[PDB]
Length: 454
Ligand code: HEM
Ligand SMILES: O=C(O)[C@H](Cc1ccccc1)NC(=O)[C@@H]1CCCN1C(=O)OCc1ccccc1
Ligand SMILES: [NH3+]C1CCCCC1
Image (cartoon, rainbow, N blue to C red; front, side, top):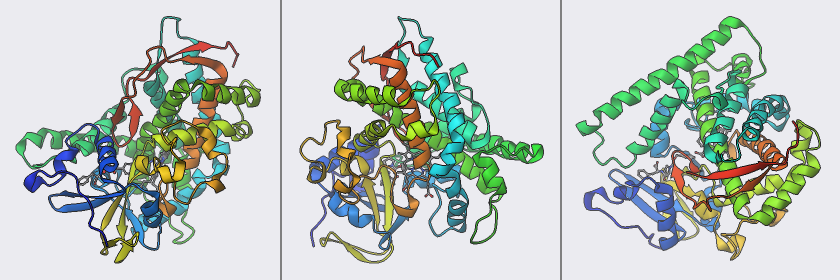
C-alpha cells in the first residue's frame, strides 16, 4: 500500500491552475514523466488519478471493476451532445439502445456501402493538390479536416459541406467549434460564475441553439422527403433495438448526428495529419508505404477490397496512433471498492484518467526505441501485451467509429502516397494544438505530382 505522488499545488485551488495552459494533455504528460505511473490531481470539489503504465491500465480496462466516467470535459460537451453515444453513461437506457441500433451501421460490412462516398471526397482532395501551382504548399490539418468533415456529412446524412469550395466554415461548424472551445476553456476557470464569463455563457447558449435548430431541420426535412439514402440518418429513422423493439426518438437522433459531426471534424483529420508528419520525418518509412500504394492501387479509383490490402499503410496509421493518439484520454470510475496494482486502494465511485500518449511510451512494453516511428512494431498483434495500445478506448465503450476512421484514413493515405511525392520544405517543428483532440498546428508540405491519372 503506497502513497500516491501529486504535482505542485496553489493553496485552495489545489492543482486546478496546472490546467491554465492551451496544452493541458502535454502538461499532464510532463507531470507523468516526473511523477511516474500514477498521480493524484485535485481541484476544488474534485479528485482524479492519472494512470500512465500498462501495468495499471491493464487493470483499469477490466470492465468487471471499472466503467466509463464522464470527465468534466465530457460533462461540458454533454450540454450539446446530450445522451448521444459518447456523452451517455453506460446505465442510461439510450446508451445500450443506440449502441444496438448503430453497431450494424459501423461494421466492416457497412464500410462496403460507405466506400463510394469516401472515394468521392478523397478524389476531391487529390484533384485539389494536382491543381496547385509550383510555388504553392499544402496546409495539412486544414485539408485533412475538409476531407473528414465532408466524408461524415455525406455518410451521416447525404449532405455536402463542400469544404473544398470554401475558406469560411458552415454556420453549424462555426457554432460547434466555438462550443467545443468554450467547453475546454471552462475546465481551468477557478470562478466560473464571475460576471466576466456572462458573454461566454450567452454565446454558448446561442451556439447550442444553432446546432439544435440546424440538425432538427435536417431530421424533419428527411422525414418529409421520404428518401431512403443509405446513410446513418436513414439507419436511425428505420432501426429498431432488438432488445426493447423501440426506435431512437428524434431528440436522441439529433444528439447522435451532433456527436458524429464532432468526431468527423476532430479525430480522423488529426490521425491523417500526424501520419503524414511522421512519413515526411521518416523517408525510409514513406518509401515502403509508397511502394505498397503503387503495388495495390492498380485502378484509377480504389475499391473496398484494395483498401483492405494496404496492410503497411494500416501499420503506419497504428504507429501514428501510438505516438499521438488524437483522442488522448478517457475516464473510468470504480464500480466497487478494489485495489489497483496491489498498492493503491480505491473506493466505489473513485475516478481514474488514462493518459493514452503516456501508456503508448511505456518502455517496458515497446523497448528503448519508444520515441522512434517504426510501423513494423504492429506486424504481429499476438506479440503486443494486453491493453498496451488503446487509441480507440476500452471494451463496450470503445470507439464505435474505429472501422469508419481506419477505412477512410487508409483509403486517403493510400491515394496520397500513390499520386504524390512529399517535401518537408520548412523542416516543420511539431506544435500540437489541443481541442477535444490533438492536431499538428501549422504543418505544411509541398506535393510533387507523379502525374498518374484518376
Ligand atoms: C482516429 C479517429 C478516432 C479516434 C482516435 C477515436 C477515439 C475514440 C475514443 C478513445 C473513444 C472512447 C472515449 C471514452 O472512453 O470516453 C471513442 C468513442 C467514440 N467514438 Fe471515436 N475515435 C475516432 C473516430 C471516430 C469517428 C469517425 C466516429 C463517428 C463517425 C467516432 C464516434 C465515436 C463514438 C460515437 C464514441 C462513443 C462510443 C460509445 O461509448 O458507445 N469516432 N472514440
Ligand atoms: O475533464 C477532466 O475532468 C480532465 C481535466 C480536469 C479538470 C478538472 C479537474 C481535474 C481534471 N480532463 C483531462 O484530463 C483531459 C485533458 C483535457 C481534456 N481531457 C479530456 O478527457 O477530454 C474529453 C475526452 C477527449 C477524448 C476522448 C474522451 C474524452
Ligand atoms: N470519437 C470520440 C472521441 C473524440 C471526440 C469525438 C468523439
